[PDB]
Amino acid sequence: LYSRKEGQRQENKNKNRYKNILPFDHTRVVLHDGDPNEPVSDYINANIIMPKKSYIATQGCLQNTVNDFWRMVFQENSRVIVMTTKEVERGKSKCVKYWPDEYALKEYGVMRVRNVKESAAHDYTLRELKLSKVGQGNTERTVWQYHFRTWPDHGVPSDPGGVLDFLEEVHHKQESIMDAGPVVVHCSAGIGRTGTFIVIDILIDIIREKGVDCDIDVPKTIQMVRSQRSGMVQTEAQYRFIYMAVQHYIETLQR
Ligand SMILES: Cn1c(-c2ccccc2)c(-c2cn(CCC(=O)Nc3ccc(-c4ccccc4)cc3)nn2)c2cc(C(=O)O)c(O)cc21
């Protein structure tokens, strides 16, 4: 019932970091208004994830998909990006740098991005970016990139505190922007770490609207996000991290 033909088309072969990890057609983010000279330009290995708050689970940029990444961010009107990995972890590239150096500006295809300010927080770096379309005039918007940089090289964090505080900030930022689009979340392949942050965010939100005693069904929620992007939450450790995060959150609310 869930096909992934687009990601399998020959023209999009190099647009996937891992030939085996592709987006479902029914939930894939379809990019419009691309270079007419490109055989195919409506593809990006990204899927919309909905539990009015949604997410875009995607892979880290490849050198040849950076422009597509910004087209997506602009198209979906996303104002918040959650990068969950370093650019390189254990000698493996997990995302090409898709943002300009601090105070610098770079043009990605028809998208102009200005890094206006970088700030350091505990477990993360926040980059305030200005995104606009070169051909237009009233398209500029701030995109807040939250770069979580303390995720361990191996396994998952032993304590969920850092991710929860991180997500709390992300949450506050998203709600401080009028009608911001889906929060973009990415990791190497866009399913393991990415799935973990999203599932946690989804569960925490439910607790924020139903109280510390509402029913919480992790397995159910995970299967729900998985019907929108396959493989979300790849390891036992990640699975357990989610359980720990929810509880830790509940226990924090209980004063
Ligand atoms: C896409 N991928 C991969 C990955 C899976 C297969 C091949 C390459 C990367 C890992 C991930 C998972 N393991 C532990 C599982 C294991 O015993 N075999 C193993 C796989 C790769 C390496 C490895 C790590 C660095 C360089 C070269 C090989 C070592 C052990 N190591 N690396 C991963 C982790 C996360 C995360 O949550 O942090 C993620 O979001 C995506 C991941």
Image (cartoon, rainbow, N blue to C red):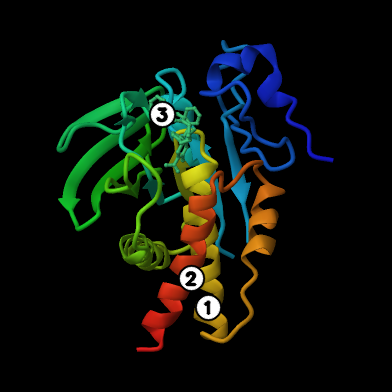
**Mark 2 element type:** helix
Is 19 in front, or is 234?
Answer: 234
Whole-percent x, y for residue 62 in the image: 43, 23
Query: Mark 3 is on which residue type?
Result: Gly
Whole-percent x, y for residue 171 in the image: 40, 65
Reading the image, the residue beneath label 2 is 246
Q: Nearer the viewer, mark 3 or mark 2?
A: 2
The residue that appears at 79% across and 39% down in the rendered structure is: 2
**Mark 1 element type:** helix
Q: Nearer the viewer, mark 3 or mark 1?
A: 1
Reading the image, the residue beneath label 1 is 207
Chain-order first, disc 2 or disc 1: 1
Answer yes or no: is residue 76 visible: no
Chain-order first, disc 3 or disc 2: 3
The residue that appears at 54% across and 15% down in the rendered structure is: 14
Quadrant showing the C terminus: bottom left
Is 95 in front, or is 130?
Answer: 95
Q: Is mark 3 within 8 Å of ligand 1?
A: no
* Label 2 with label 1: CB-CB less than 8 Å: yes
The quarter of the image that holds ligand 1 is top left
Whole-percent x, y for residue 102 in the image: 16, 37
In the rendered image, the vertical position of residue 95 relative to residue 15, given as above or below = below
Reading the image, the residue beneath label 3 is 135
Crowd tier of the residue under label 1, counting other residues whose Cα lies within 10 Å: few below 14, some 14–19, many 20 or above: some
Query: Mark 1 is on which residue type?
Result: Ile
The CA distance from mark 3 to mark 2 is: 45 Å
In the rendered image, the vertical position of residue 4 relative to residue 161, given as above or below = above
Chain-order first, disc 3 or disc 1: 3
Quadrant showing the N terminus: top right
